[PDB]
Image (tube, coloured by chain):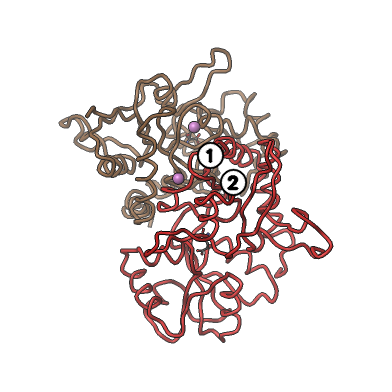
Chain colours: A brown, B red
């Protein structure tokens, strides 16, 4: 029937511009883990689709004042897209307003440092002031710190929320640049999936340190009650069980890694 | 209103008999990760409940001939329990017949050996015949091997399905005993969660080797369409985000580990 509108986000290696994108149109402009996953889910569910990059470049948060959702979550809530296929964390507040598949990838929050930075853990970050640290805006990592009752994470949030200049970034790439350019004086808190990808990219100057701070998952999201949710969830489980999700992770993370 | 009937399974450290169980009655007979999780979910959802150990001691599989489900899955499908709170793997075939929460624990299939056994991987097992290996009956690990199209896992299944004497066991404890007693000539394929627990128990003679073979999760299950599913799923996500699931994992795996 109708073309399914897929909201997604330009986040490497999930969705990236193809080298020759300026000559290409439509879905062919893009490549990556989520582009491949969208093709697999569409094939299993039997729909045609159009990939659309979220206008505001955000994952999704609800404004405390207006109660309005932004980002990909907002695109689903307000009826501007039919499905989100992206590294979108399954969270309580989001689950209350959109539907999610079972997870297609497991992850947790992690620490990225410039190589040689003397930090091995969140506790280490929390006990010093020389090295600044922050998170992405409008996403689940920022919310993790804002809501935590665990002393070390509350201490980190109390620092981050009032730090000057701001420690928060608008995109993962801006966080990576800040780590790379800050001579060891900025560390970035981000999901293990993104951190592990970046560690395999030139110039090979970052690394993931410490254990993950939490354990959670990304899911494919649909507007609440959409008939697409049920077949999409069954497709995710099938792809998981057939080993396809594992093959795609290796393809986009490790197969052409650049750091040895 | 009505007392919720919870089906569960005696699998350490998820549900275990308390030391003084012979003097105790009802839910007080039991302790463990799933006993604590049931209490937390009941508190958040506001129900009273009765823990019941599944009669046949199985997780759940569908008989190819009769199409009848056994185990905890069968208890839900046939209306004998209201909810399953257990280390029950979220799988495609189960998702088609019962509802599941988002996962409360992440895991994958793994290899348990007696210390000193010269095996480091599934590929190693598959390329030799001196060391026998098998899985639990009536569960998701056996089904993983039976359905895999990946050459190494298909080769392992072709061996396991015809091995004599049988390499399959009825309970995890029987698998552990077979590893411990077989002088290095049996290796057991089981979920990483169970393997990591057993590695911390006396006599400290087993170990987990190699990476996990897959990535998946346990969920709380309800009969399809039950009104309990929605609040239970929101409770799982809340407990996840508050760090309670992490606290319970540490409590039952590591806090009183016996092997250093
Ligand atoms: N996956 C996150 C974005 C990344 C982050 O917050 O670190 C989300 O869905 O909000
Ligand atoms: N968690 C598995 C049981 C253990 C196994 O198969 O290794 C299930 O739900 O079937
Ligand atoms: Li939801
Ligand atoms: Li289901």
Q: Hey, which residue is sitting farthest right in the picture?
A: B23
Q: Residue at x 46, y 81 (%)?
A: B166
Labels 1, 2: one chain = yes
Q: Hey, which residue is sitting farthest left in the picture?
A: A23
Q: Residue at x 42, y 29 (%)?
A: A225
Q: Is residue B162 left or right of residue B43?
A: left
Identify the residue under disc 2. B82
Vertical placement of residue B227 versus A260, above or below: above
**In front of the other: B162 or A260:** B162
The quarter of the rendered structure image containing the N terminus of chain B is: top right
Mark on residue A136? none
Q: Residue at x 48, y 75 (%)?
A: B168
Q: Quadrant of residue A64?
A: top right
How far apart marks 1 and 2 lie (CA) works out to: 8 Å
Q: Position of residue B105 (x, y in %)?
A: 56, 51
Task: State the count of labels.
Answer: 2
Q: Secondary structure at mark 2?
A: loop
**Contact, CB < 8 Å: mark 1 with mark 2?**
yes
Q: Position of residue B144 (x, y in %)?
A: 41, 63
Q: Is residue B147 left or right of residue A64?
A: left
Q: Is residue A212 left or right of residue A51?
A: right
Identify the residue under disc 1. B226
Q: Position of residue B212 (x, y in %)?
A: 47, 62
Chain letter of the residue carrying label 1:
B
Dot 1 crowding, Cα within 10 Å, few <14, some 14–19, many 20+: few
Q: Quadrant of residue B183?
A: bottom right
Q: Position of residue A113 (x, y in %)?
A: 53, 44
Chain letter of the residue carrying label 2:
B
């Amino acid at each position: 029937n109708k073309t399914v509108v897929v909201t997604t986000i330009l986040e490497s290696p999930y969705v990236m511009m193809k080298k020759n994108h300026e000559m290409l149109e439509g879905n062919e402009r893009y490549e990556g883990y989520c582009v491949d996953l969208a093709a697999e889910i569409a094939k299993h569910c039997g729909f045609k689709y159009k990939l659309t990059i979220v206008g505001d470049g955000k994952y999704g948060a609800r404004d405390a004042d207006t109660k309005i959702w932004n980002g990909m979550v907002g695109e689903l809530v307000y009826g501007k897209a039919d499905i989100a296929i992206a590294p979108l964390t399954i969270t309580l507040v989001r689950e209350e307003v959109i539907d999610f598949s079972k997870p297609f990838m497991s992850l947790g929050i992690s620490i990225m440092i410039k190589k040689g930075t003397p930090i091995e853990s969140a506790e280490d970050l929390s006990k010093q002031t020389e090295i600044a640290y922050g998170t992405l805006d409008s996403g689940s990592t920022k919310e993790f710190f804002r809501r935590s009752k665990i002393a070390v994470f509350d201490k980190m949030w109390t620092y981050m929320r009032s730090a000057e200049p701001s420690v928060f970034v608008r995109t993962t790439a801006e966080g990576v640049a800040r780590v790379r350019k800050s001579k060891g004086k900025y560390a970035y808190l981000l999901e293990s999936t993104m951190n592990e990808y970046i560690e395999q990219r030139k110039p090979c100057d970052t690394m993931k340190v410490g254990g993950n701070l939490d354990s959670k998952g990304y899911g494919i999201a649909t507007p609440m009650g959409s008939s697409l949710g049920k077949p999409v969830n069954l497709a995710v489980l099938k792809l998981s069980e057939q080993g396809v999700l594992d093959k795609l992770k290796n393809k986009w993370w490790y197969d052409k890694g650049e750091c040895g």
